[PDB]
Amino acid sequence: TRPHASISEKVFCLIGQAEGGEPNTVYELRNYSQAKRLFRSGELLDAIELAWGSNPNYTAGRILAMRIEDAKPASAEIGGLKITSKIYGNVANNIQVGLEKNTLSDSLRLRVIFQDDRFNEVYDNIGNIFTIKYKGEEANATFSVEHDEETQKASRLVLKVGDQEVKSYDLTGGAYDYTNAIITDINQLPDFEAKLSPFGDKNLESSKLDKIENANIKDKAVYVKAVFGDLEKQTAYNGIVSFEQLKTIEPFELTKLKGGTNGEPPATWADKLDKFAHEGGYYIVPLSSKQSVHAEVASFVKERSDAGEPMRAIVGGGFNESKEQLFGRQASLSNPRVSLVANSGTFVMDDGRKNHVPAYMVAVALGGLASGLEIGESITFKPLRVSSLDQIYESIDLDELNENGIISIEFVRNRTNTFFRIVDDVTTFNDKSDPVKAEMAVGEANDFLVSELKVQLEDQFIGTRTINTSASIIKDFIQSYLGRKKRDNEIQDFPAEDVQVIVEGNEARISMTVYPIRSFKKISVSLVYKQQTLQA
Amino acid sequence: QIYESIDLDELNENGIISIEFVRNRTNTFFRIVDDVTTFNDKSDPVKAE
Image (cartoon, rainbow over all chains, first blue to last red; front, side, top):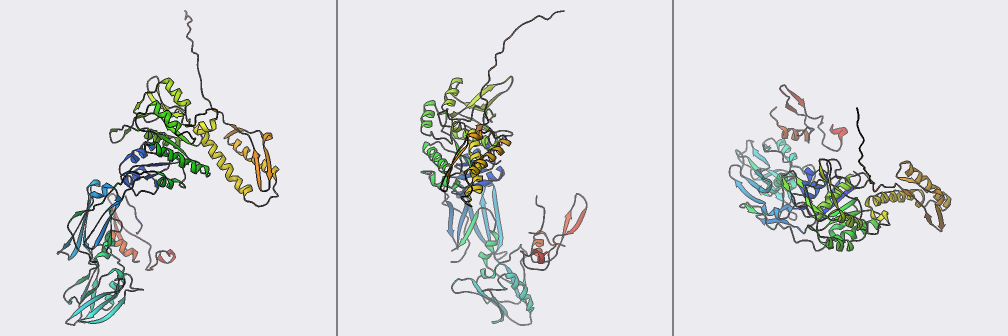
């Protein structure tokens, strides 16, 4: 590998169908060029590119995703070789592989086809690592290679003068573990010859050679053949397929790798949703309509948040859902840290397509916006990508479903432009006396403040250094820290007189009060027309 | 200097200094492709470089 030239803090999570990538592993997608390379097709790809494309400036952050399927690979067992596919799904059934042995080279030849990616390859001079020959005066020369009787790894290689062993190389271990050493040291018994292959690098570990005897030599040049040892080099980084040796290798006609399986749908998402526990997400969205999956996601979000790791979800159901379904689903999804989306629509992508967008894909679009916006700012009135809104929701309806905590999209008719811009960051929790639960952005600001508070209280006091730092000092430390957050304007002011601390044994209880940065909900303007004369 | 890019990788890995042909816009020149020594170990740059 000689030197050359060759030519957002809120993480967002996803889980849905995709025709690519191994399931039950959360991937981090560095760039949507790499997303398509992993997630070939399916709703997850549209959900990734919709999220990063949802607005020309409020782009989404670092995405984590997983294919939720019971998929398994396509494979075949033929000749001497088990052939297996790194793609899991029905797409693997399109793979084809076939061998030949070529009398022009006395080598093996391999061919791999994969029409889906318009991908095709041929490998030739497979095996036949390096040449041996004899030039000394004698009438006869040969050689041999032998195995360990147990492992069937190679153990000896020997040059023979006629029938008899001249010198041996310890393939069981040491300086001769790499065939390069033998390619040199055969040319340190210069009556014999060895010479390298012209067809690219090989550097085979000599233990992978195969047992051979008494090939007749002087004029002739003969290879050591070691076909599987060479195939490991030819398949190091190559294509979609991998190989395992059972038995002895032989060619075989072109044949499809079978057993490619997307798999049955999941009966429950819980044991595959658990992988997003410790991965640093904050917004997670399911790409599915079933209410049971939504209840499970609500449960997972609660399980992580109650453990100190805050998380939230945005959810939408099916297609063109009606009011009765939204109320009944809100009542079945009532806990905070969950948002329900009420509207469907159409989105445009660069392929020239107009999708019919389910409600959980509008959540993704909103979730990508929520992650793009810097901490504490509301999703209120930010314009969205929508091409057409699918709706039975008028002015008053938006009041109904806003007051009942369902997020919705509203239509605006400016002087010239008509654009869609989403209403308010209210959550599924209904009781609007408690804005700390109701408004998602208020909850975000709270979650990150309490976490920073909880963290710095570890170093200062929960480090356990002594009991002799009493409760007047803890009160002072919370006043100090509220001062620092007041300096950054994240809390407007705090009544230091109304802070109290109680201590018993090795436990402190503290009461406090904070003034939140007060929001601005409404304006109304009385515009009156009058006339007065111009004169000359 | 017929040795090609894959040959340069084989000579360089084995610790043998090689030379390369390079084409500019119109001019050309020959440059030396690595400061490697004859030493074996790849994780010991004090000796390998």
